[PDB]
Amino acid sequence: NKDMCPICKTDRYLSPDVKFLVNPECYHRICESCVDRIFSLGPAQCPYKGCDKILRKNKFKTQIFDDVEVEKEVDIRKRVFNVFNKTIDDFNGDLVEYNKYLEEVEDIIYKLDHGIDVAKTEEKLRTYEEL
Amino acid sequence: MKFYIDDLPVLFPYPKIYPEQYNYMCDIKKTLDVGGNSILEMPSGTGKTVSLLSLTIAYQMHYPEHRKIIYCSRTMSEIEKALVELENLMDYRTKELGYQEDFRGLGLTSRKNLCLHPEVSKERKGTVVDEKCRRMTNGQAKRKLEEDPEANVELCEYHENLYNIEVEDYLPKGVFSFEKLLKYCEEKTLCPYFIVRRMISLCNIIIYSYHYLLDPKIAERVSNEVSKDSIVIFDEAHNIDNVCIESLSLDLTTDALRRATRGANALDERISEVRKVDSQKLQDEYEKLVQGLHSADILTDQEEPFVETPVLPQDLLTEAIPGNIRRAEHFVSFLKRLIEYLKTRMKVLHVISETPKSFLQHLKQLTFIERKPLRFCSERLSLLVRTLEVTEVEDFTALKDIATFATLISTYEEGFLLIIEPYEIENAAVPNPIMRFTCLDASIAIKPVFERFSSVIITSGTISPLDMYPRMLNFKTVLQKSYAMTLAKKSFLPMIITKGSDQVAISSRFEIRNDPSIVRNYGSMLVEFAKITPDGMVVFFPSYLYMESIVSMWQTMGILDEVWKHKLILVETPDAQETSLALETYRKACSNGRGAILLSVARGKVSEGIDFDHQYGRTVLMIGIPFQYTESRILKARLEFMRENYRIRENDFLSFDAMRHAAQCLGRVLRGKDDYGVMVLADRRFSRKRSQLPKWIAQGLSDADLNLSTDMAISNTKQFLRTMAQPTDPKDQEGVSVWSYEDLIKHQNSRK
Amino acid sequence: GEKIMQNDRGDVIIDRYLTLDQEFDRKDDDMLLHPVKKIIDLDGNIQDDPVVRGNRPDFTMQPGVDINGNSDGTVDILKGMNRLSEKMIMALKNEY
Amino acid sequence: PRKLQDLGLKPASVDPATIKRQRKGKITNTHMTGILKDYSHR
Amino acid sequence: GNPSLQNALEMARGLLLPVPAHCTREVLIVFGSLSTTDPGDIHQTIDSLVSEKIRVKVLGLSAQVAICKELCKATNYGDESFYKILLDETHLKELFNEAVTPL
Ligand code: SF4
Ligand SMILES: [Zn+2]
Ligand SMILES: [Zn+2]
Ligand SMILES: [Zn+2]
C-alpha cells in the first residue's frame, strides 16, 4: 500500500512517524522505524516476502517520485550519467555523433532498467568507467 | 454614394456619411499610403466597420498592388457582423458598377461552428468535434477503406465531395457569411470548414478571430497561407493582450497529472503491443528522425499533428531530434519521469514564483532532463501518436497538455513565469494544487505579426488611452487618434453615481460586497432605473461571483419582486447555450415591449461581441468599476513585469484595464446617431477616472454629473428620455452630424 | 427563487414533487433549447478556438462553491429565473 | 480533547467544562388603579 | 393594474371590423406606461392590424417605447411621425388638438 508500511503494519493515520524510505537495490515501501529496527545491528535480507536480497542500512533514502519504476529509472540514469558525461563540446560539434551517443546512453539505461542484458551492460559500464 | 479621397474612388453603401466616417477613411488611407501601424478610436454608434470595409475594398480594387485584407476581430459574432456588412457593401458595389467583379471574402471559424455532419453535430466540445473530424478525415481512414472495402471505418461525405471539384469551384464569387455558407454547403453537401481552409489563399479578404493570428496552436497554418504583404485590420483591439497572454499561457492540475500518468501508461502499453505485432512502423520513424525529417516532412498536408505547435514558428528549433526521445520507449520514459517531476513539484505547501530557467535547472539536477529534448516534446508525441495510429486519444489529451507545457517552458525563459499554488481556490477545504505557466509579456505573441505585416490598423470603439498600447505592446505607431463624434443633440448621457438616494456611499470592492447599505442602494437604483427605462436595460457587474452574491441577496431582500413587476430578469449563465437563449429572450422582450433587464458580467461573454442597439440598450448600468482580483498571483506577476519593463504602474495599469472594460461595456449601447441610451456608472471611484474614459464618452460626460446621487440621476435620466423621445430636427442635423454627397463635396473644397 | 436550505421543514406531501419539478425543468429545457443566429451565438464565440488552454480564471469568474467545493445553489436561482422568463416569452409564441 | 492535537491526531471533541468555563412606590393616581397597564417593554 | 397593448389592439380590431371600407379605421392610444404585459404575440396583432388597414397613433407619456414606435410605423406605412411623446402640459394639449384633424 502507498499509505502504510507493510513490514511494521502501521497506518499513516495513527502513526505519522512513518516515512517513505526505499533502497536502490530493491525499492520497498518501508519505514524509518523498521529500518532502524532491522538494519542498525547489521546488513540483512529484504523483509518483504518473496524477496531475499542483501542490503545495507546506509544505502536507504527517501523516494522522490511516486512511481517505483520512475524512481528506479532515474536512479539508474544517475548511475549511468555519473561516468557517462560526454557533451557536444566533447564531441567537437558533431551533432549526429552526439545524437548517436545519446542513443547509446538511453539504450544502456533501458537495458539496465529492464534487466534484459544486465551482465553484458554491467561489464561494458565497468570497462568504460575504468578509463 | 461614390466619392473620391485623393485619387481613390470610394463606394459607400449608404446615401449619407458621417464626418467621423470620412475623417476615419482619410486617416486609414494616409496610413496605407505611408505604410505603418495606426491606432484609431472611432466613437461607437458610427459606422466604424462599414467605413473600414468600404475604404479597404476600394483601396484593394483600385490600387494596382491589390493587397489582400486580413480582418481580425475578437468574437465570432463580430466576424459574422463584419461578413454581413461586407455582403451589403459588395451588393451595393455590384449595383453601382453594373457587374459583380472578381471578389472573394470569407470568414473563418472552427469545426464546431462549421460542421454539417449529422453524427458529429451534438458534441458539446470543440476538441472532440475536431478529433472526430480528423478520425474521419486524416486520409488514413480513406486509405484503409480503399485497401479493405469492408472496413468498419467511415468517411465524411461533405469532406469527400470536395475532392470531385476544384478549389476555385468550391463557392461562387462573392461574400459568404457563416449562415449563408452553411446553407450553401448543406444544399450542395460540402464541408464549409475545409472549403474555407482550402481557399484562404484565394480570398481578397479573410475575416477571423484574434486566436487564428496570435495563438500559434492554430495560427501556424493560417499565417503561412495568407499573404505576408497584406493590409491587416485589428478590429476591437482593446482586449488584444488577453488573447496574446492566453495564447502562451497554460494551467496544470493534479487531475491533469493523474490522467497524464494514465495516458503515459496506456501509451507504453501501445508501443508494447505494436512492437509485439510489427516493428517496421516504428523503425521507419527512427530512420526518418535519424535522417532529420521533422513533423512537417513526415506529416502529410491533409492530416494534422496530434499536439498543436504551442510556440512561435521562429522560436521552434530547426535541428534534428537530440536522440534522448527518438525511440518510442525512450520518449515514453522521458515523458513519464517529466510527469513524475511535475507531481513532485506540485506537492509544495506554499506559493512558488519561479523562472523557467530555474525550473529547467531544478529539473535537470533532479531528473536529468535537458532543455533541448523538451523543446521537441510536442513534435515527438505527435509523431509517435501518428505512427501508433491510435483510435482513442481521450487518455492522450493530458499527454497533449504535458507536451504543450514542456515545449512552452523549454523554449521560453524571458517574459514568462511559473506559479505553483497550493490552493487553487481558498474556499475549498481539501487543498488543490495548481501549476500555471503564465506569459507576462503580451508583446511576445504579437511581435511576429508586426514583423510580418507592413500595415496594421489597430482599431477599437473604446481604445483608451491610446499611448498605452505602443508601450504595452512593442510596436511603433505612425498615427494614433481618437475621434470626437459630432452630434446635433447629445445622443448619450454618461452619469457617474457616487452615492445612493440617502447619500450613503456606494462601491463594489470585493470585501464589502455583503454590506447591506450598498446592496440596498444598488437594488433601489436598479428598481428606479427599471421603472423609468422603457424597453431594455443591461447591468454589468465586476465579477460573476459578485453578481451571484448580490442577486441572491436581492432575491432574499425582495428587490427582484418589484423588478419583476416591470421587466423580465435574465442573468448571464456560465453555460453558453443558456446565455445565448437568455440573450435571445432578452432581445425578444425588448422587441415586443414587455421590458427586460439583462444582468451580465463586465468581463464575461456578453460584454464582448454582443451589441445592445436601440431597444436592446437604452441603459448600461455599471455596478462599480470592473476591477480584476488584485491579489491573484498571475495578475501581480504581470503588473510587476509591466513595472520593470514598460514603467507602467500598479494602480495605473489596474485602472486602465478596469476602465477599458467599463468603456467596452458602455460602447455597446450605440449603433447610429439616431440611437440613444444612458450610461450610468455606480461607484465612488469613477469620479476620478473621467480622463481615463474614451474621448467621446468624456465629451458626453459633463462636469456636473461626476458626483451624482441616485434620485437626481433618475431625474436626469427621465429628462433625457423625454427629450430624445421627441423627433429631432432635420434642419438641425442636415449638415453638421451627417453629410450628404454635396455636403461632403463642400467639406472637401473647404479643406483644399 | 429563494435559496433552498435544509433546516426548513417544507411539507412532506408537496416535497416529493421536487424531483418531478426538476424533471419538468429538464423537459422545459428540451424544447427551449434551439440553435440561435450567429449574431448571438456565444457558444460558437467560445468554441471558435477549441484548443485554447490559457490560464484558468480566478474564483470570482466561476460560480460560488461551498467548503467542500460543491455548488452553493446561487447559479440554480439564476437558471430558474432565466427559465421563467423564457417560459413567459415562449407562452406568447402560440396560435393566439 | 486538548492532548490529541499534542499527539498529532485531530480531536473530534471540544474541551469539556472542567478546563476553562465561567420597588413599588405610592400611587397618586388612585382613580385608575387597574385602568393603567404595566409596560416593561417597548 | 398592468397595461395590455395586445388586448387593447385586439378589441380595437374587433370594433373596427364592422366599419365600412370608405370609413377610415384609426386607433389613438394614450399610453402611460413604459412596458406592456401581453397574453400572446403582439407582432401577430400588428400584422393583423396592417392587413385590416387600421392606422394607430400613440401619444406616449413618459418615453419612447419601441413596440409602440414599430406599431405606429407598420400601421402608418413607414411613417415614424405618428408616435408622439409629450414634453409639457401645453405640448400634450397640442398633441390632443393635432389628433382631431383627418389623417
Ligand atoms: S469534414 Fe467538415 S462536415 Fe465532415 S466532420 Fe469534419 S468539419 Fe464536420
Ligand atoms: Zn515499518
Ligand atoms: Zn527486496
Ligand atoms: Zn480558575
Image: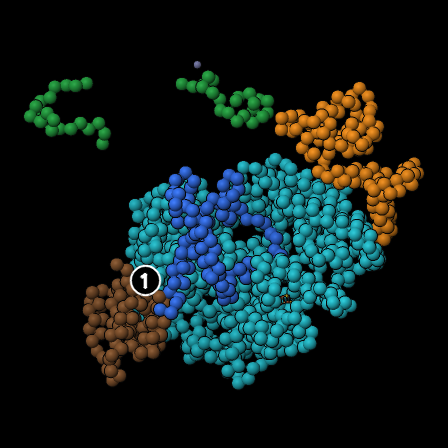
Query: Does residue B650 appear left or right of residue B197 in this picture?
Result: left
Q: Position of residue C39 (x, y in %)?
A: 49, 65
A16 to B495, vertically: above or below: above
Identity of the residue drawn at 33% across and 64% down: E39
Q: Which chain is cyan?
A: B
Q: Which chain is brown?
A: E
Q: Position of residue B152 (x, y in %)?
A: 71, 64
**Which of B636/B337 is in front?**
B337
Res B481 visible: no
Query: Does residue B701 appear left or right of residue A3 in this picture?
Result: left
Q: Which chain is green?
A: D
**Which of B528/E25 is in front?**
E25
Q: Position of residue B452 (x, y in %)?
A: 65, 63
Q: Name chain A's colour.
A: orange
The quadrant in which residue A123 appears is: top right
The quadrant in which residue A6 appears is: top right
Question: What residue is shown with label 1?
Answer: E37
- Residue farthest along the front direction in this orientation: C13
Instruction: Tally the numbered discs.
Output: 1
A55 to B305, vertically: above or below: above
The quadrant in which residue B155 appears is: bottom right
How many residues crowd around disc 1 within 10 Å: few (fewer than 14), some, or many (20 or more)?
Answer: some
Identity of the residue drawn at 65% across and 61% down: B132
Find out if the beta carbon at label 1 lies less than 8 Å from the nearest ligand 1 atom: no
Q: Inspect the image, locate mark 1, and give the three-letter code of the amino acid beneath it.
A: Thr
- Residue farthest along the left direction in this orientation: D31
Q: Name chain C's colour.
A: blue
Considering the numbered disc 1 on the image, is that residue within a helix, a strand or a loop?
loop
Q: Position of residue E22 (x, y in %)?
A: 25, 84
